[PDB]
Amino acid sequence: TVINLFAPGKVNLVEQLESLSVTKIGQPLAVSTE
Amino acid sequence: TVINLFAPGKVNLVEQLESLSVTKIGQPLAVSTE
Amino acid sequence: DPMLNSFKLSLQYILPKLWLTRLAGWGASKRAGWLTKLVIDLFVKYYKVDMKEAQKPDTASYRTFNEFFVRPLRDEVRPIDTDPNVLVMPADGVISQLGKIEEDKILQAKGHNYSLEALLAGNYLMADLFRNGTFVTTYLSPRDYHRVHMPCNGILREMIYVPGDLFSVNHLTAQNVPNLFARNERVICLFDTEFGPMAQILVGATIVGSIETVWAGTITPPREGIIKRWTWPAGENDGSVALLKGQEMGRFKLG
Amino acid sequence: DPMLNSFKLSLQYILPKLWLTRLAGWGASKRAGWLTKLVIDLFVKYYKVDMKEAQKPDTASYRTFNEFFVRPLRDEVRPIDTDPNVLVMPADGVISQLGKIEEDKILQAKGHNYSLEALLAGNYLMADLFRNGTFVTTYLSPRDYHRVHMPCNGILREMIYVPGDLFSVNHLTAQNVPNLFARNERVICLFDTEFGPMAQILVGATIVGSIETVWAGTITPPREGIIKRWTWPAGENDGSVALLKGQEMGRFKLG
Image (tube, rainbow over all chains, first blue to last red; front, side, top):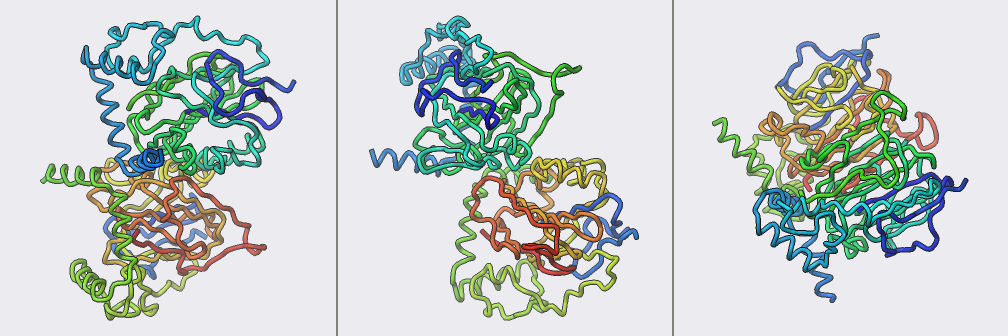
């Protein structure tokens, strides 16, 4: 199990990703707010 | 077991004290440098 | 079902968690031709491991069980999103929870959240970098491929090792073990990246307990039982450390 | 003899140190008349307790066993020194090691030292306060008093509970278990005083695993396995806590 932490308002996760969503390495997970 | 820490220059402990010395509460342990 | 869920949390709570880890870490680290292969074979059979994703699909080419456990995939089967404004997934698995960190509280399971200070072992300075932020908890099933890659181009700053217990870390525990990730032995990697300070942690389990990075090697074992802390330059320095998006940074192991 | 030892400390790390502690804690915290009195009498006879100094020297006058353990003394027997320019000893026992802390490395026993950081659980700010200062370490034999008192007037600023193992802190383990005080369960107390800052740390034994301060009561057990930390004002402020040279600040207990 690995966990990532980020700044308050310097990024935004993918709204489609909820709990139990399948996770593979090469896929995108979040995107900046700039 | 108890452990104590002090600031670098404020306190000198008793020179006659070493390992296996007898530790009773009311007895002196360290004298201020002022 | 209630019996199994009972006995599952039962034997968990009572069995010598540290001692079972040692045996697997010593068994999976010794070399024996067919058993290691046969164990890998029964491992893939029972857990339905996708052995085709690997760079070496033949289970006989793995000397020990740990070498297969740290099997390298084919680089072409995990294509990295090259958009520099997005962050790639860390490693294969499933998501436990994710979302906003509501004032130094991070959701674990339904009716269970854990503190941010508790996760970072009292380092309040690091916690303030992530108060009212966002997070993502990613679980790795034994079937999954057990190495981690970077979500973005990052510069290594701090690393903090925490000694702790060795729990199952399967979901049945995550819904019943309070502060599961702040208790178990874990390794903290603090990063600098264009999107601000990013953290990436690695938490072990009741047998999957060994943690290693590409730059430091096998951190645990040995389990020494105290908090270790290193720091690194801030990039562009003699000895600075950085690494790219989707680049292999660490891996779990049996030990 | 040298390896007669080297299977006595082998006995140390195998036996389920935690489970025995909690078992012995349940036993000593229960209401037993003649049982405790018999157990107390044997204890008094084995470790040669000086019951004369006790405030209540009839072994029957104590209900449970932990009460006999946290026995308040005849205050007439422990005289806090007069000189406000001397710091008085903190607790009864025998001095383990003392002297100057030489650049963050404290002498544990001959051939073993531990970091000021790993003791303070990575609180490098608190560690940076005491680099190249002084220290002292006191071993509390079972015969001795078991409450902890202040060496000087103090104003509470921080307190940190640290989880960890429960090895015996006797000298035999002190000369062979590395970073014993940095691994075993402990509670750190940080004061301001007229002689810079001062830290007083309580560390539990292999069944003497309970630690309570006077200002917060019992802190462990429960052994929640993470790090708790609170903060206080600068003194003479709303919610400020202070205590004087010789006051009881805490005590050890079975459990």
